Length: 294
Length: 294
DNA sequence: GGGGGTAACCCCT
DNA sequence: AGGGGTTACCCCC
Image (spheres, helix red, strand yellow):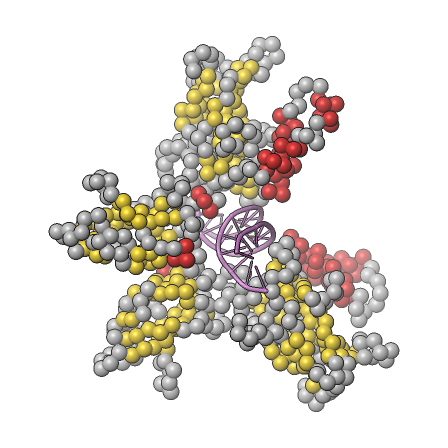
C-alpha cells in the first residue's frame, strides 16, 4: 500500500448525505458535490493527494457502483473540470501535490436511458486495455452485461473513483497508480435518503416516568428506518428510544412518539437530556434538540 | 328550451375525487362516476332525450372549463370509446336515457399537447374540400393551438354530450344542441386533493384564547389553505386558525394558534367544529371537534 | 379498480 | 445555487 510505491489518499471525502443528483433537464449549474466536512461557514470539496512522488500528475474522477467489485456507474460526473463526455480531471503541479474537485455534479440517467448509456460505456472499456474491435459475439455479450448490470445497480448511490496518472514513455500520462474509491454518496432526492433534520417538536419537557406523547416534525424519512434516540454526554452513556408504530410516522414528515423512561426515577432537580433522529441502518443522526425531565 | 328535441343531464359527473390517468399508468383504473355515487350504490353520468322517441346515438367528449366550449387536449377512454376519443352510447326507442358507466380521462403530457391539439383541430376543421384547404390554412390553424395551450387547464374538464338523430337521408348525422356538464377536477392535481385531517396534538383549549396546535393533514398548498372553526347554526359563527405559510410543514402538517370563541366566559366548556378549507375552492375536510373550556 | 408511492421535471428568488 | 413543488410514471393488493 504505502511502500509498494506512489499512491493516492483521499484527504477529504465527499459528503455522504444531503447532495442532490440532477437530471440533465433540470439544468447544468445547481451546485457542487461538497466535502464530508463542508458547511455554509467554510466550504470543503472532495480532496486527494499523491504521496511518495513529486512532479506533474493527472488525477481523473469517475462514478463507480456501491458494489465492491467497482464497476462504472450509469451516472456521470458533470462540471467545470469535465470534458464533452470525457470525465473530470485535475492536474497536480509539483509543489502542491493535492487536488480539490470543487465543482462536481452527478447527472442522473433515466431508467429509460440506462442500458443504452451503459453499453455506450462498456464499449469504451472494451476498447481501453483490450484490442481495437468488437465482433458481433463481442457485442451481443457486452449487451449481456448491460442487462444484468441494470437489474442490480442502485441509481441513488455512487462512489467517486480517483485514478491518478503519471507521464509514461512518450510523456503521455497513461501509466497509472492503484485507484482509490471513496465512501458512498446518497442522492438526497431518493426518498428519506437525505440527512435527518428536526424542524420543530411540540413538547420540550416531560415526566421522568416517560410515556409523554410528542409530535416531531422532520424532513422526509423512511417509516421503517428511523428512530428517536435520547442520550446523555457522560461516562455513563445512557440511551433510550421513542415509542412509535409505522402509522405514527405521518406521510414521511412527522413522527408521533411516546417519550422513554429516564434511567433513574426520583430526580431531586430537573435534568436536560438530548434527543436526535437516527437512521436504523447507517447510524447518521440529526442535530440534537434538548428535552428536560421534570 | 321546449322548441325542439333536446338533451338533459339526469346525473352530472362527480366534480371531485376522480383521478385522470396518463396513458402509461394503465387502461382500466375505474370509471368517472355520478355526482351522487357511493360505495355499493354507484351512479354514472346520465343524460336523456326529451321531446322525441326512437333511435339516437349520443357522443361525449371533453371540453375546456372556459365557457366558450372548446375541445380539450385530454380524451375520454374506455369501453364505449372509439379511437378518436369520442364515446357514444345508443339510446333505444323505449328508454331515452343513456348512462356512461365506464369513462376514463387520458392525461396528455405537455410534450404531447401540441400534436394532440393540431390533430383534434384538423379533424374538427375537415368537412369542405379537404385536400387543398388543409395545407393553405394549417399555419394559421397552428396559431390557435399555441395560444390555446398556454391558457388551458389540464386539471379541469367538462363532459359535452352531443345527441344525434337518424337523418334517413344517409343516417345519424342529424344534430341536437350540445349540453355541457359542470366541471371535473383531477384528484391528482395538488389543487383538487380531498382534504383530510389525520391527527392533532390538542383537542381542547381556552375559550377566547389561541393555543398552538400541531395538525397532521393530507397534502395542502401553503398559500391556499385555512382552518375553519364553526358551529351548527347559533349565529352562523366562524373563526380561523392563525398560521403563516412557514407554519404549513412540507404540505402535511400545520402549526397554528386556535382562534378565540365568539362568547367569552361561557358557563361550561362548549364543543365546536374545525375543518380544513381551501381558500378559493370552498371544498373542506370532514370536521373534527374542539372543545373550548373557561 | 383503486391506491400509494417513486421517478422525472419545472421554475422561483 | 439551492430549493420547493408539480408532473409523469410505476406497481402492489
